[PDB]
Image: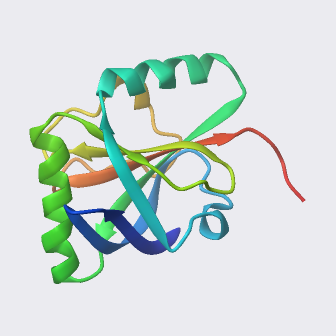
Amino acid sequence: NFIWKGFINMPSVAKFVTKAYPVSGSPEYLTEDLPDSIQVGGRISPQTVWDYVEKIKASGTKEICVVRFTPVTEEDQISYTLLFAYFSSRKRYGVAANNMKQVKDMYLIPLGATDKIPHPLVPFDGPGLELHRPNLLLGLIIRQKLKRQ
């Protein structure tokens, strides 16, 4: 069902358990590669991210993988909403800090219930997102293109 269950930690703002579900791209090997806790260690301008995503689609060198995070408990929902409010108000995305197995970069993106899906994730190669949804924290995972053992 879900790809990965663990923490999303931003020091001195919020941290909570969450489960990740596929949205677009290949979710293969994410279960083993992702750590038990994802440290989010700064903000970034969204257009700096979408330009990097544009050049990453021209070069067939890395694959985009979008996932959807949901809180597991209602006390995790209190912090989930806090982290969504931090990035949505400042109009920014989050960046992961861990040195992970294959993730070249990972970006946490706030997506409001009624906001239009950003243009660079345009058609979803996966389950996608329903029309009626709550405020969501989206995971933009960037991984090197290869086939493994």
Q: Nearer the viewer, residue 119 or 4?
A: 4
Q: Nearer the viewer, residue 20 or 36?
A: 36
Q: Residue at x 85, y 54 (%)?
A: 148
Residue 70: image quadrant is bottom left
Q: Residue at x 61, y 61 (%)?
A: 30
Q: Is residue 135 above or below residue 24?
A: below
Horizontal placement of 47 versus 83: left or right? Answer: right
Q: Residue at x 50, y 19 (%)?
A: 54
Horizontal placement of 39 versus 10: left or right? Answer: right
Q: Residue at x 68, y 50 (%)?
A: 102
Q: Nearer the viewer, residue 54 or 16?
A: 16
Horizontal placement of 33 versus 70: left or right? Answer: right
- Please indicate, yes or no, whether residue 8 appears anywhere in the rendered image: yes
Residue 105: horizontal and vertical position, in percent?
54, 41
Residue 40: horizontal and vertical position, in percent?
37, 54
Outermost residue, front direction?
12
Give the number of callouts. 0
Q: Is residue 81 above or below residue 139?
A: below
Outermost residue, right direction?
149
Q: Is residue 129 above or below residue 28?
A: above
Residue 29: image quadrant is bottom right
Q: Is residue 5 above or below residue 83?
A: below
Q: Quadrant of the C terminus?
A: bottom right
Residue 121: horizontal and vertical position, in percent?
42, 31
